[PDB]
Amino acid sequence: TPVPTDFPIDLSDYLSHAVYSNKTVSCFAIYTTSDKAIELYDKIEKFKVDFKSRHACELGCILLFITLSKHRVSAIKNFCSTFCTISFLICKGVNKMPEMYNNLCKPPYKLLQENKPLLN
Amino acid sequence: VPTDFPIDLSDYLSHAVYSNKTVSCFAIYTTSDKAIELYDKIEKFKVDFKSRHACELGCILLFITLSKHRVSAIKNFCSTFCTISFLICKGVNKMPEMYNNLCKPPYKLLQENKPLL
Amino acid sequence: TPVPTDFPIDLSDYLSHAVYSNKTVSCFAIYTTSDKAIELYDKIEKFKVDFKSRHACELGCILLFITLSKHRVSAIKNFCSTFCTISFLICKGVNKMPEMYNNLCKPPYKLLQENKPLL
DNA sequence: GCAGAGGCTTGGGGCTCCTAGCCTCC
DNA sequence: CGGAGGCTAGGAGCCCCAAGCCTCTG
């Protein structure tokens, strides 16, 4: 098994790939195992989220969410890795949240997930 | 409910408030469940020794790290794991005596990665 | 003005002259100014003091006391350099306490104030 | 028997990064 | 737009020293 490295390509365009940025976005998405995803579904409630949801992805499980306060992409990644028990994890800020959600409800992607429907 | 460690072992602990010192060995005091969890979720510091212990209505996990950490950095670390579980963490100065006192009559030993020292 | 440094020689045998010693004594003696002493007479009460007495030297007064808990001669020396931020004072541990007080009552000196008689 | 010397042991704190927000430019 | 990147209050790691403790010895 690859793991792999980054988000699947079919939605890898909807993401922000900035290593040299300090911008504090409000929208984030993550990619781990459905198990590690299930647990992170609760930890996120430290940044007081307005919305959150976990979807079903091929050979993984993506969970996106949005907070009220702005935060760093790096700040979120560093926060989740605290639970990383030899498990894989990748974090990137979503520039277009509405496009992402609907894309995770297509064919290769399902739901289970969320909390609220429309966004801000 | 219990804030600050019991008195019988408050002499082996460090009660610094305005210190920026970095020590390697600590001791945390939380519920029995958070104790078990923070036993493995602490291996992210590449510890040398960790030992499960128990107390009156709570459990204490003392441990040591090859790297030097601040006592306030350890309380901020466990804080991210717990949410309901009470968190009172103080570094230990007399780790040998501490270890022993937690194996005496009123206490006991549960699990230990490596013997002692 | 003939500014003085260090206790007068006529009593420099009742004092501790240790400079490289980490020892912790009990009885201390300060040699500052008249009102500088009267000041420290209270500012020292922050040390849970048992006995304390103010005497009169020559160029000023001499504060004498005993702390319930031991301390460094340097610990007090530094603590006295906190309030005055001026003037001149000498802080040294008192090796011969009973003998000390005696001379400070002898004619060359005189007692000015003591919260309790020493025993 | 002192009295001075270091042997130790802690907390305080002056620094020097790291972190993770803030921001505005192109 | 969305990166890049400056700016800074706390977080957290360096180090030392102040001020206690102690036993030793000349």
Image (cartoon, coloured by chain):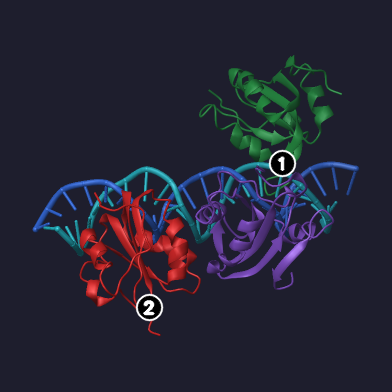
Chain colours: A red, B purple, C green, D blue, E cyan
Tell me residue A92's x, y (percent): 30, 65
| In the image, farthest residue toward the bottom | A1
Mark 1, Cα crowd under 10 Å, few <14 / some 14-19 / many 20+, is: some
- The answer, for residue C39, to whether it is visible in the render is yes
Image height check: is B11 above or below B102?
above
Disc 1 is placed on an element classified as loop
Nearest the viewer among A99 and A88 is A99
Cα distance in 3D space between marks 2 and 1: 79 Å
Q: Chain of mark 2?
A: A
The quarter holding residue B66 reads bottom right
Residue at image location 24% in from the left, 67% down from the top: A103
Label 2 packing within 10 angstroms: few (<14), some (14-19), many (20+): few
Residue C17's mark? 1
Quarter of the image for residue A15 reads bottom left
Indicate the position of residue A16 as horizontal and vertical percent values.
Answer: 23, 65
Q: Which mark is residue C41?
A: none
Q: Amino acid at mark 2?
A: Leu
- Residue A14 in picture, x, y percent from top left: 21, 67
Question: Horizontally, is B74 left or right of B55 in the view?
Answer: left
Q: Amino acid at mark 1?
A: His
Q: Residue at x 50, y 71 (%)?
A: A85
Q: Nearer the viewer, residue B103 or C14?
A: B103
Q: Is A86 on the left-hand or right-hand side of C36? A: left
Asked if residue C16 is positioned above or below residue C40 in the image, the reply reads below
Q: Kindly report which numbered mark, 2 or 1, lies closer to the viewer in this rendering.
A: 2
Relative to B19, residue C112 above or below: above
Q: Which quarter of the rendered picture does the N terminus of chain A lie within?
A: bottom left
Q: Nearer the viewer, residue C48 or A114?
A: A114
Query: What is the number of the mark on residue A59?
Result: 2
Percent from the top left, x then y, of residue A13? 20, 70
